[PDB]
Image 1 (cartoon, helix red, strand yellow):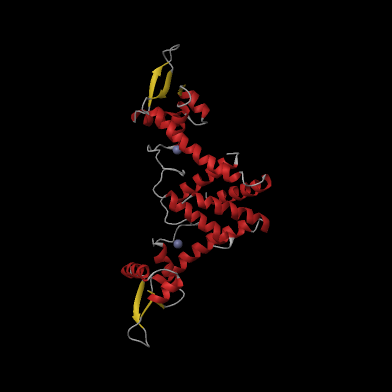
Image 2 (cartoon, chains in turn cyan, brown):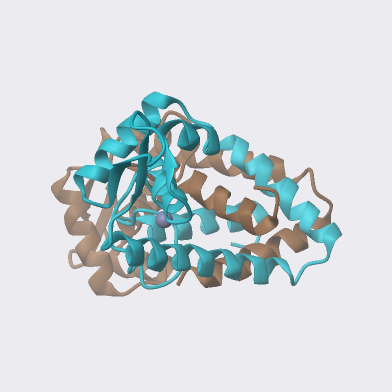
Length: 146
Length: 146
Ligand SMILES: [Zn+2]
Ligand SMILES: [Zn+2]
């Protein structure tokens, strides 16, 4: 609608219809089939880069042992990750991706990367002063939604 | 996140979580209980202001007779509107809200009005040049979502 208030309202409407029956907000095929919680997904992506421990994971993603534990449980049940014993210390447990998960992580990261780069490109059309205005607009509108 | 691309991505995430299991994007109680399609809702709101005909409705909301018809059917089944015969011409059918619907329309309009005024207030913090930037940002980002 022509007022900014109306435009803002229509834009949210557009996003709502787009998010309907989707797991995340992504641009593209939505061919990132598997449906993971944010934590599970962060862990998956984290392990896709490096083998790590329960405490290393909690640290890296600034979450509690409880949360890491619950997430590792689920990922393991879905055969996306697998535990193994630290070559140097029988007591410490290492985690990593299963074979079938490696490409699943890759394909789904790309999707995120394509979505981010589209936002980057749109952003690049605006000067720094303009990006600041957009930024202050998004923070303030973000506050209304909690 | 600090880049604008990351901020844009987080902002959409925020809206997605907010829209989850909601009918529309509204600020407030969500105590606008009844769930109507956009057309049904537009008709309800339209009839809340004025009694009108099938062809008057189609005109006003720029939609087809088929669409008006389907919408009137549903609204009537839910006892939100009621037909009556034009005092001046037995052939033309008038529509209007039922008693129980009058306050339902009012309460739900207010909700929309409160949501719009919040966007208006946020918008008023920005000069016209800044609102133009925001506007051009929203149009372009809107295009990505279709
Ligand atoms: Zn994802
Ligand atoms: Zn509504």
